Image (cartoon, grey):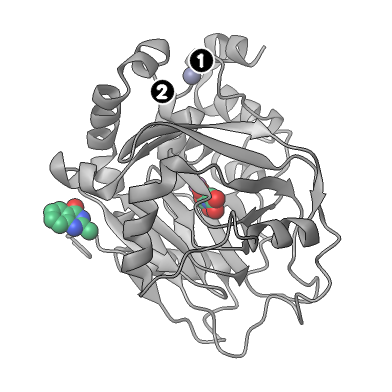
Amino acid sequence: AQNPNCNIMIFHPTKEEFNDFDKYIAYMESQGAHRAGLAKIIPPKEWKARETYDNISEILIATPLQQVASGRAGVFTQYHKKKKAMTVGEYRHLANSKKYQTPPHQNFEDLERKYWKNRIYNSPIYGADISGSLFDENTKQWNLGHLGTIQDLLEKECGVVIEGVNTPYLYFGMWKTTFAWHTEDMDLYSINYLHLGEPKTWYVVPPEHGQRLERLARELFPGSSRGCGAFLRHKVALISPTVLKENGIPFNRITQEAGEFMVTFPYGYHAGFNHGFNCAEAINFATPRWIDYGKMASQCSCGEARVTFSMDAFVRILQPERYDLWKRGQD
Ligand SMILES: Cc1nc2ccccc2c(=O)[nH]1
Ligand SMILES: O=C(O)CNC(=O)C(=O)O
Ligand code: NI
Ligand SMILES: [Zn+2]
């Protein structure tokens, strides 16, 4: 078996290899990349997402989210407090202000130490889940707005035609902005391109060990666990690498820099934080290997994790037995 220790693999495709997206994902998996839950892809030196990022300041962040923490440094939840709209230019200025800017640090490891020591004592503001794309329409390779759709994948694999669409989301981050432990909707893949700015550090649990993380989460957030059989779907729980190690949870870490892609694989739990002002673009996608994960994906039915229009059809077709109870949480 390839990659038995479930290490995060890093790929350097040639421009020729960068033409066929599906084929390269399949290649990565043939090398065992999916066992880690996360892979890095460094694009060919000839490739660019777009010409410049000089004219992005007038993008609107309609609902910036202030991420307020509760708990202890290594085991906490965050809730999102809605703030007034601001442009990306205004957001960048805020990110760089004395209150929010990245502190002096020696290296990525030093900054990681500072993050887990001090994150809960601050409330950074995130521009998340903004529908849109920063890929030039003339960028033909690995353009996250031009991928084959999950709906068409389901149709190709299973022969059923369904409603729904599948578009990218932009994320504007600052120091300490945080993404909680989660797998994707319906345990889909995700692909994430860091367009511009400071790095993003990722943590990931191998898919074959996802249930170990779930068990620890139930122990660490016992009230949440009683309230919902899949509360990590709420995307609000954080557990530090120190606490993961103390509890023997297998995981890996890696830092993504501007110009690099990350792919998360089905049922690969991940979490992380931004180093400073940045912009990422991400979208879910599927492959034939995803279908069995989609069938088995655990759902939030307590209702906290609202399920999108498009995910309705996934549950309806792949999980017909759960559909009724699960749609009540939606309604
Ligand atoms: C990144 C990582 N380091 C470890 C060190 C000791 C024991 C376990 C781990 C682990 O799961 N991940
Ligand atoms: O970048 C973020 O804040 C969150 N991204 C993801 O969880 C992802 O790409 O799957
Ligand atoms: Ni994700
Ligand atoms: Zn729930």
Outermost front residue: 98
The three-letter code of the residue at mark 1 reads Ser
Q: Quadrant of the C terminus?
A: top right
Is the distance from the Cβ of mark 1 to the nearest ligand 4 atom less than 8 Å?
A: yes
Q: Are marks 2 and 1 in contact (CB under 8 Å)?
A: yes
Residue 183 can be seen in this image: no
Question: Which is more N-terminal, label 1 or label 2?
Answer: 2
Q: Quadrant of residue 296?
A: top left
Q: Nearer the viewer, residue 197 or 192?
A: 197
Note whether 166 is above or below 193 in the view shown: above
x and y percent of residue 221 in the render?
A: 32, 23
Note whether 186 is above or below 245 in the view shown: above
Q: Can you identify the residue that label 1 sits on?
A: 301
Q: Nearer the viewer, residue 212 or 312?
A: 212
Q: Secondary structure at mark 2?
A: loop
Is residue 29 left or right of 123 when viewed as pictured?
Answer: left
Kindly identify the residue that appears in the image at 72 percent across and 47 percent down: 130
Callout 2: few (<14), some (14-19), or many (20+) C-alpha neighbours within 10 Å? some
Residue 98 can be seen in this image: yes
Q: Nearer the viewer, residue 43 or 69?
A: 69
Q: Can you identify the residue that label 2 sits on?
A: 230
Note whether 253 is above or below 155 in the view shown: below
Is residue 181 left or right of 32 when viewed as pictured?
Answer: right
x and y percent of residue 67 in the render?
A: 56, 39
Q: Nearer the viewer, residue 239 or 249?
A: 239
Q: Quadrant of the N terminus?
A: bottom left
Is the distance from the Cβ of mark 2 to the nearest ligand 4 atom less than 8 Å?
A: yes
Spatial CA span between label 2 and label 1: 8 Å
Q: Which mark is residue 243?
A: none
Is residue 188 left or right of 152 when viewed as pictured?
Answer: left
